[PDB]
Amino acid sequence: MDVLYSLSKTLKDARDKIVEGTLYSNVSDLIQQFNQMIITMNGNEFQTGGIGNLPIRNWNFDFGLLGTTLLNLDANYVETARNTIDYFVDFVDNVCMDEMVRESQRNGIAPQSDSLIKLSGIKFKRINFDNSS
Amino acid sequence: MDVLYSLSKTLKDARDKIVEGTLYSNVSDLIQQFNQMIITMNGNEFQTGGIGNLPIRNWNFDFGLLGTTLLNLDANYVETARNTIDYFVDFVDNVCMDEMVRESQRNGIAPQSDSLIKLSGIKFKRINFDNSS
Amino acid sequence: EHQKEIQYEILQKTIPTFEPKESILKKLEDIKPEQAKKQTKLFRIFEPRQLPIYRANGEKELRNRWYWKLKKDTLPDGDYDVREYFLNLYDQVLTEMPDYLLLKDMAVENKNSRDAGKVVDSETASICDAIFQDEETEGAVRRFIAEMRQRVQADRNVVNYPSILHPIDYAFNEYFLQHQLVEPLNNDIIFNYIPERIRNDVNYILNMDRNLPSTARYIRPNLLQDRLNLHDNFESLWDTITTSNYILARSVVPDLKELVSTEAQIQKMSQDLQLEALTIQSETQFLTGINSQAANDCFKTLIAAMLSQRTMSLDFVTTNYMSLISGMWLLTVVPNDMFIRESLVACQLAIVNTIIYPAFGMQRMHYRNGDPQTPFQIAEQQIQNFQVANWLHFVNNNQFRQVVIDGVLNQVLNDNIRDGHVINQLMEALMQLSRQQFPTMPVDYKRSIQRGILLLSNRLGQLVDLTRLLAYNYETLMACVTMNMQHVQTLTTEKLQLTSVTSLCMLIGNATVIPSPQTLFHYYNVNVNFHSNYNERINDAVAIITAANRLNLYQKKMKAIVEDFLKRLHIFDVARVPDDQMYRLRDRLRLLPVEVRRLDIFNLILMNMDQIERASDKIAQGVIIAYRDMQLERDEMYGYVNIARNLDGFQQINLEELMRTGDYAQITNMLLNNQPVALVGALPFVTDSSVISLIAKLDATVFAQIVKLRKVDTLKPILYKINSDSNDFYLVANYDWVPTSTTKVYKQVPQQFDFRNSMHMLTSNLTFTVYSDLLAFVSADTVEPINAVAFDNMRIMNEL
């Protein structure tokens, strides 16, 4: 679960600190964290939806890491990035919603969805960070 | 006083950004700040309470620091850390409460408690950090 | 011309440019930065030795507890000297920076125990066998040592070997593992380390031949950009770079081929030229020769100039009008933008005046220029013949369209498709010429002039070819330049005799030459290394300087580091580096981050700094005087001694401060009216066993000294290692009594040894194979020259 959290603060602190004009070094510590993610992900496939009117969409990962063009980012850098973020956003949305509908009497404190159950897996823990929310 | 502040944002940004898994280079800038503290403290004795129904608990300092190696964090790393945090938490609580009751006609704007008066000392100033609250 | 020299040189002393031309090339092809960096030893700082221990008031208790001690304990006297000492460690750390690591290469037999237990390194081994036998070591110890077996996983390449280091040691070696700075390697990556361009340049063939084990591993090249904008102030050094980058270029630029026999052309030339026809100033237009060379020189020279972002002038020869015509060629192409304003000055006006204007009949007012903004231009606004008129705007523009960001960050001021191979420029440069045939002055003039012009025109069918050539070449070579390249007005020129120019021109046939594959790489490779070195040293540099500051080393900082820096860069010979330059260089350096690597380590050293210093056997931090009979304390290790683990209750006087700043006797007064006081920092040391001594109150002596003259180096203080043994002086415990030490010291006690906590496990990868050079794996051929093509795709060099 905590996993999930990160995924976002990653994107927020991303769609926020990554803009046309900021010095690289203001995101050095960040950039890293990001890439680290892409890696852990790529390869594994997911299933969301499959209930009520909720659509069953299939997500797959195949992304290239992030460059580092020195001395403040050039517009081009952003757009090639934003394109990658938007797939994760539209993803998480579907992930949240899918686990935001399932309920369980016995153990209704743990992950239900096929999507999240897979995240609590150990091979992903490598992402967790900045738990200030 | 401002001193006090830090002590916390230190712990929060700590009990928050230090979790099983995260990449070190997200806390490099942090870890440091932390240690710096332990040092300044170790070798000091404090005392809180003494008024009304407020217990008089005593505190001492003598702690080891934290590794700097490790790409990522292993569970073991955390637990050996959390154990040290919990002593500071239970500490600050007692520190706050002790200075949160005393009032002074004269300088009701200055520190009161034996605990805090000692903090405004110069030798502790080396701990200030991130005043955004 | 002697007067010209002295000064032309007084300038050359403000240029860290090495002397000979060639002498520079070597320096480059020589820079072999890349280096596999491996290591053997685990690396520590301290092993654990046995030591005698006497219980309170006791003799050698017979036991010998294990304590940690420093291998190589060389610590200076004085807080300051200490700080400097550590600093050297930083330098040592970097020079030994193990880029990667493996453990099999350190395997060792854990002599004792079932399960073929293998352990980390030699020291690890020793220790085990050692303790195994110190009979007073909990049954759990042998056990652990015993059964603890290595961890070998064939698949995945994992190796977890049991080891024993130390808190501060694990500290190091650890990060060294977590920063193996070694990324994988797939055919695809090799393919990719190739300019996004070349691959698509048909003319060049690509192919793979060797495979790649999942064992493949390389080290990032690290090609950050400029970081340092030398483009706006360090002229002296740019000139030296340009020069360099320039020679480099010539070394590459392919030599030409298939030229027209020198003799043949010049001969039809005399027929056409009508040389000796009255005109007094003969045989100045034919010093043109040695063209079989001049062209090769003019050619090379031209490229490098460009690439290297150099700027030049022209060994111009006013009379020789022809030589001028060709000039027009030059501007038709080479973006005047990179031509010191002046040499262009002469050239144009020489054209403008002794040409066009009068032979064309226009301004018979020849032209009067003081210093507007581009004399060559303005001519436009007032010329009535379109053809002529287009040349003008295009030439006064063609500003070397300084705007590009290709294949990922490569600002390489580009050039017109037009020029490229649209060429027409040439066709138009000609058409305009095709209608310059008319009146004004003597006959032998137009006759001679126009006739020469025609030789440009006919040949024009070919002159085209020239355009294409360069177009490609520059447009090719360039691709493989990492260093960015802002256009700058170099301080130095480069002479280009219209002689050669003119030759190249009417003297090139259906030749067709291009950069040999192997050639190209070699080029990349170099700039690469160089870069790597620049960037790297930069980091090495910064790291130090910053450390130099918190490490309060208020001394060297200026030059010291800078000197070494430049030297390693090779390219230039310091010395002739104006002083405003070296310092300014620091001014810029000090304002940058620090390669995590570098930085991350210093942060570590500082945290343990304190601990080391007191950990040493010789030297403690300051002493105390109380002129109050004091009770000697007792510690298991030193026996009966006068140690104090804490100051508090007595002023502190930074020896360092005092010594460095002279004395005001504040101390002199306190000592004199005999007052409680403390001294802080690192200090000499003295052990003594003379029970008697204590009685004689020796410790209250040494001090008076200082006073004399400042100094305070000669301040050896005293300790009384009074063990209930090695002290012949023991008529002490035989008499009821207690130690009356008037003084004691700060050296905190060494650390006890606790196995458990020093035993760490080890995460090491297993079995690599490191590769350098790279490229090599690339198989590449080349079409036959007669079949080239540019962006054009029609065919470079196409005048069958």
Image (cartoon, coloured by chain):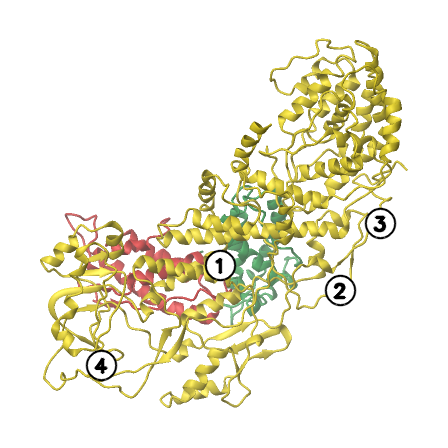
Chain colours: A green, B red, C yellow
What's the chain of the residue with tag 1? Answer: B
Q: How far across and how far down the image is residue C725, in percent? A: 22, 85
Q: How far across and how far down the image is residue C325, in percent? A: 77, 23
Does residue C672 appear to the left or right of C159 in the view shown?
left
- Same subunit, tags 4 and 3: yes
List the residue tagged with mark 2.
C210
Up the image or down, C642 lies above or below C226; here it is: below
Give the position of the N terminus of chain C as an image quadrant: top right
What's the CA distance linking mark 1 and mark 4?
50 Å
What's the CA distance linking mark 1 and mark 3?
50 Å
Residue found at x 49% / y 89%: C112
Residue found at x 69% / y 28%: C315
What's the CA distance linking mark 2 and mark 3?
23 Å
- Residue C723 disc label: 4
**Among the two numbered marks 4 and 3 on one chain, the one whose residue lies closer to the N terminus:** 4
Nearer the observer, C379 or A44: C379
Give the position of the C terminus of chain C as an image quadrant: top right
